[PDB]
Amino acid sequence: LYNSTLFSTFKCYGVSPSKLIDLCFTSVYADTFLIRFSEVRQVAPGETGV
Amino acid sequence: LYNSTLFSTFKCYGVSPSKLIDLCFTSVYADTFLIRFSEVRQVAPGETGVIADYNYRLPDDFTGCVIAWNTANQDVGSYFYRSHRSTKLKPFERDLSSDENGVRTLSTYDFNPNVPLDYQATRVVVLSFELLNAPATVCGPKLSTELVKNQCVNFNFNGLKGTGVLTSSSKRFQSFQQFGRDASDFTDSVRDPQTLEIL
Amino acid sequence: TCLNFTNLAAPAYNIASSSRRGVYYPDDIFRSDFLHLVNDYFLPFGSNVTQFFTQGTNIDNPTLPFRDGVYFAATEKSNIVRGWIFGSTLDSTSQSAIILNNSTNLIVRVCNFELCKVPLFVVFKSNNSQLSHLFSDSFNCTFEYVSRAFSLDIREQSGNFVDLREFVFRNRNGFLHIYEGYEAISIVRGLPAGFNVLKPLLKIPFGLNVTSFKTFLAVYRVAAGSISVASSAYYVGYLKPLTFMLSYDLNGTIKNAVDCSQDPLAELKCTIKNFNVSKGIYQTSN
Ligand SMILES: C=CC1=C(C)/C(=C/c2[nH]c(Cc3[nH]c(/C=C4\NC(=O)C(C)=C4C=C)c(C)c3CCC(=O)O)c(CCC(=O)O)c2C)NC1=O
Ligand SMILES: *[C@@H]1O[C@H](CO)[C@@H](O[C@@H]2O[C@H](CO)[C@@H](O)[C@H](O)[C@H]2NC(C)=O)[C@H](O)[C@H]1NC(C)=O
Ligand SMILES: *[C@@H]1O[C@H](CO)[C@@H](O[C@@H]2O[C@H](CO)[C@@H](O)[C@H](O)[C@H]2NC(C)=O)[C@H](O)[C@H]1NC(C)=O
Ligand SMILES: *[C@@H]1O[C@H](CO)[C@@H](O[C@@H]2O[C@H](CO)[C@@H](O)[C@H](O)[C@H]2NC(C)=O)[C@H](O)[C@H]1NC(C)=O
Ligand SMILES: *[C@@H]1O[C@H](CO)[C@@H](O)[C@H](O)[C@H]1NC(C)=O
Ligand SMILES: *[C@@H]1O[C@H](CO)[C@@H](O)[C@H](O)[C@H]1NC(C)=O
Ligand SMILES: *[C@@H]1O[C@H](CO)[C@@H](O)[C@H](O)[C@H]1NC(C)=O
Ligand SMILES: *[C@@H]1O[C@H](CO)[C@@H](O)[C@H](O)[C@H]1NC(C)=O
Ligand SMILES: *[C@@H]1O[C@H](CO)[C@@H](O)[C@H](O)[C@H]1NC(C)=O
Ligand SMILES: *[C@@H]1O[C@H](CO)[C@@H](O)[C@H](O)[C@H]1NC(C)=O
Ligand SMILES: *[C@@H]1O[C@H](CO)[C@@H](O)[C@H](O)[C@H]1NC(C)=O
Ligand SMILES: *[C@@H]1O[C@H](CO)[C@@H](O)[C@H](O)[C@H]1NC(C)=O
């Protein structure tokens, strides 16, 4: 995805980035939705907001 | 630069801001390049992405500051970046190979004011410094005051400590060091930074 | 322009053993009467290095690997060994850095060099002893350094090696660290056993992927026109991740060191952190 996508937010919890290459995950799930640009900061553990 | 510039990013590592005024840095280097606005978050120690491993990589024990600001309506040409590589780069390393023999490795982006905010051109300046037992030659705007002795005073020979100051006449220095080192990782008998008199 | 050679002999990878050689300062902090352990990259005590010499119809300048750091030591009289080139694949497809001494200036420059097969300096015995070409071409690049001018003697035959120059090269965070040391000698055969610390000299920012290196030599052209080589030798060793135990004294100089992985006595010395051991039986760490 390096030459086709541009991500403005990439935050990982419980595992550091640049370590996902040499790791195996046993149960992966993906959740998708669509919000406003200012509400991305509310998608985090222990946050508040609408 | 307070009445001329406006920085969107000012993050320092290994030293807090509002302390750079009263500090001296021995070896100072500046790295300059140009990326998109959304890729500024990748210029950090320990990050991932197309910039952090194929174009520019910071060491883990990094000391310095990262400064970025948007420069639309100033940079209009077409610029290039590395999209893929066989391996990832070492810290503070370059790869000037414009193309491989098999396939081209350099992808391009075009910068224009009409392009969206996520794809706009910003300038990034990265500084790096360290502190040794040597003259620094890069200091802040501090004025030397009167030297007093035989009292409990706080001295600022590039480092803060509050003791009593006397005259030393039995010290042998190596003409590089300012303070030296003791057995318990202590610094004693500091030097006047412009003279050779050892306190 | 570069020369032609057909009577060159293949190098013989002779084996000579170092002994307490290749110790450099790890930190720029003045310490006196100190003693502490350091885990870094060092040349192992008692390890064997490879021998290359230029004696007769035998010029030995091959491309050698740059794994984790190189110990370089040269025993010469007539200034045969001049400098080195560092880089990857040593051609025009990538960038390479040189450190050179052309008997007038010290040259530090990294460009897109195109090296020939046998890069040598040529000195005329007659004709007031000028220098000559090194390589073919080098296009655009982004670094320069020319030092001050000096005069260098470029011919002397004493019969015995009188100079010993030792170097340690390291690559870390885009910097090339250089540690230097000099010692007067009088030998005929090989690498003398001894001990001398090396001081930090250079720190050049390159940003280069360094995997190989090659050395620059010098030869002589006789008045008839043929080439004649002069006696010289150099040795190459590699650094390994090891634990050492250095000592400091008055004036803050390193005077002794112990490689903790050599023998059980060195392990015992590193365990109790002392050069002198009394009689008894002691438990040692690994
Ligand atoms: C290109 C790398 C290079 C380095 C880093 C270098 C360092 C270097 N060379 C010398 C002297 C120094 N260097 C040389 C010559 C050489 N020294 C060598 O490492 C080599 C390869 C030659 C040439 C064959 C001489 C003949 C002297 C003595 C100069 C004097 O008598 O003042 C010093 C001490 C200066 C002083 O205290 O007077 C240093 C730091 N020389 C170099 O050429
Ligand atoms: C981004 O990179 C991918 C490969 O990672 C490119 O996809 C290739 O495109 C060529 C033509 O340029 C095709 O022949 C290949 O079959 C493609 N490979 C794969 C694996 O799909 C892609 O073109 C690049 N550019 C963009 C804009 O997406
Ligand atoms: C930002 O501040 C600097 C520093 O005061 C200003 O430079 C001064 O400009 C005036 C005229 O406006 C001159 O008389 C002074 O000599 C200048 N000072 C120096 C130190 O050169 C600068 O004009 C200000 N910029 C803006 C855009 O307001
Ligand atoms: C530094 O350069 C070397 C030499 O080109 C690179 O090693 C090559 O890696 C590729 C990866 O596909 C191999 O195909 C080559 O055979 C390797 N060459 C040798 C001589 O072993 C190395 O990857 C480069 N290092 C970095 C960090 O980019
Ligand atoms: C320069 O240093 C000298 C002592 O070396 C001192 O007397 C003098 O005031 C200094 N000058 C300035 C302009 O700071
Ligand atoms: C090298 O070798 C041959 C034989 O000496 C000579 O004819 C040829 O021109 C030379 N090649 C060069 C100088 O490139
Ligand atoms: C050092 O000598 C030993 C003797 O067993 C040999 O195996 C080894 O290859 C030598 N080291 C090098 C680097 O050639
Ligand atoms: C050494 O190289 C420098 C590079 O500027 C040059 O000026 C000088 O003439 C050279 N000296 C020689 C070839 O003797
Ligand atoms: C002597 O040196 C000059 C100047 O480099 C050169 O032109 C000439 O050919 C040389 N002569 C001999 C006989 O080597
Ligand atoms: C050097 O010049 C060549 C030939 O003109 C060019 O293709 C190349 O991009 C240049 N290298 C740079 C600017 O780094
Ligand atoms: C320390 O330096 C002084 C300088 O005069 C010298 O005389 C002395 O021998 C040195 N100390 C040692 C232990 O070599
Ligand atoms: C300890 O060993 C050193 C050599 O490492 C020797 O010179 C010295 O005499 C020994 N004894 C004492 C008490 O220092």
Image: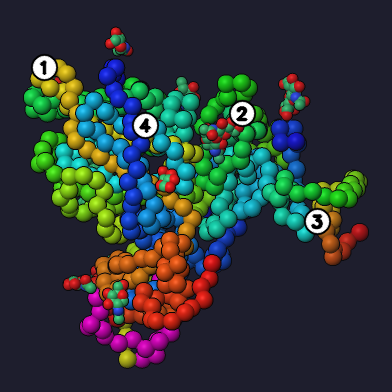
Q: Residue C87 placed where, x, y %?
A: 43, 36
Chain under callout 3: A
Which residue shows up at 47% across the image and 43% down it? C67
Which residue position is annotated with label 4? C62
Q: Residue at x 17, y 44 (%)?
A: C188
Residue carrying label 3: A41
Looking at numbered disc 4 in the image, what kind of residue is underneath it? Pro
Could one spot residue C258 in this view of the protein? yes
Please tell me whether mark 2 or mark 3 is closer to you in this view.
2
User: What chain does mark 4 sit on?
Assistant: C
**Spatial separation of the CA atoms under disc 3 and disc 1:** 82 Å
Instruction: In the rendered view, tell whether residue C247 sits above or below residue C51.
Output: below
The chain letter for the residue carrying disc 2 is B
C220 drawn magenta = no
Q: Is mark 4 within 8 Å of ligand 4?
A: no
Front label number (1 vs 2): 1
Q: Amino acid at mark 2?
A: Leu
Helix, strand or loop at mark 4: loop
Viewer-closest of B125 and C135:
C135
Identify the element where label 3 is drawn. helix
Q: Are marks 4 and 1 on the same chain?
A: yes
The residue depicted at 47 percent of the width and 38 percent of the height is: C211
